[PDB]
Image (tube, rainbow, N blue to C red):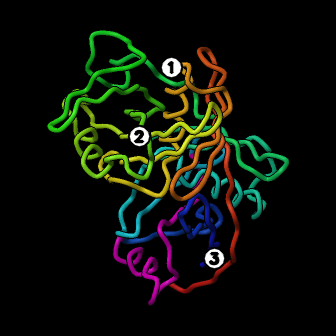
């Protein structure tokens, strides 16, 4: 079986052509392949497959090092696009792909960066979903240790965005879990902590819904920028610095879809039996 090793935003991936290859992985096998000393070594495994839908080009699955399938909105998108482009599985510049719990259109930029159309930000509290009497640019959320202000929005998934003075000292450790599992968020939520450097630059940390802090949250990045823009604190093109890497977010506001642009790097090609 053939595979490629890639990296993007602090995560290293094994990417597999599941279209021209028939591939199956047990959680077990995945755990073994992920092992850095006895296996290939990787944070995540990405499998490209047929979409079984005439209006899409591909579908792809993501698995964690534990061996279980995951559905982290937008991650692996850059590696996926670069991969199908490098492997010649397609030659289109605009690629439509489905994810376990989502959908998106990717654009292979001329400079070789990958631009993702994340759709239009969802503000309606009910549609996030988030419990509140009405829309607000800033909501008041109470926790056991502090009352915080936050912007709330949905990029398909739910997000909670809190601004902080210093990204490194933000109380992510305590506030993260408290917001992530907060009562007013029926289906839970992604908790973003954003430090605004200037109108086009932010530093961000995110406590992922049901996963805690990660090196990078694509959707988190989108959400934080959408909120900042909504509140008038940010311009329409913002550089976002996540722990694992940087992303460029572009959003022209209400009535417009939000774009997430970033890089993906091919490291090597591999061959492995079983």
Image location (x, y in percent) of residue 2? 63, 76
Element marked by disc 3: strand
Disc 3 vs disc 1: which is toward the camera?
A: 1
Q: Is residue 175 above or below residue 26?
A: above
Q: Quadrant of the N terminus?
A: bottom right
Q: Residues within 10 Å of mark 3 (few under 14, many from 20)?
A: few
Q: Which residue is mark 2?
A: 192
Residue at 66% in and 26% down: 236
Image location (x, y in percent) of residue 274? 50, 84
Q: Is residue 131 above or below residue 146?
A: above
| Image position of 235 (left or right of 192) | right
Image location (x, y in percent) of residue 229? 56, 24
Q: Which mark is residue 231?
A: 1
Question: Residues under labels 3 and 2: Cα distance?
Answer: 37 Å
Range of residues picked out in magenta: 27-51
Residue at 43% in and 39% down: 165
* Residue found at the far bottom of this picture: 38
Q: Which mark is residue 32?
A: none
């Amino acid at each position: 079986m053939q595979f490629s090793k890639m990296h993007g935003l602090g995560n290293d991936f094994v990417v597999v052509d599941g279209v021209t290859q028939n591939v199956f992985f047990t959680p077990e096998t995945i755990r073994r392949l992920a092992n850095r000393h006895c296996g290939i070594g990787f944070d995540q495994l990405l499998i490209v497959e047929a979409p079984y839908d005439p209006e899409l080009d591909f579908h792809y699955r993501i698995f964690n090092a534990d061996g279980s399938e995951v559905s982290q909105c937008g991650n692996g998108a850059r590696c996926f696009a670069r991969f199908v482009t490098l492997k010649g599985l397609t030659n289109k510049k605009d690629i439509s792909v489905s994810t376990q719990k989502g959908n998106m259109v990717l654009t292979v930029k001329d400079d070789n960066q990958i631009r993702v159309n994340m759709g239009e930000p969802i503000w309606e509290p009910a549609k996030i979903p988030f419990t509140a009497n009405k829309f607000e640019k800033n909501y008041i959320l109470r926790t056991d240790i502090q009352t915080v202000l936050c912007g709330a929005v949905s990029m398909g998934n739910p997000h909670c965005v809190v601004q902080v003075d210093d990204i490194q000292t933000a109380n992510v450790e305590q506030l993260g879990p408290l917001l992530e599992s907060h009562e007013r968020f029926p289906e839970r939520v992604n908790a973003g902590f954003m430090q605004i450097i200037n109108k086009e630059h932010i530093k961000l940390r995110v406590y992922e819904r049901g996963a805690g802090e990660t090196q990078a949250s694509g959707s988190g990045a989108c959400a934080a920028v959408a909120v900042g823009i909504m509140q008038g604190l940010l311009n329409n093109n913002v550089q976002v610095d996540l722990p694992g890497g940087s992303l460029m977010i572009e959003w022209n506001g209400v009535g417009h879809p939000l774009y997430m642009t970033g890089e993906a790097t091919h490291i090597y090609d591999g061959f492995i039996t079983l």
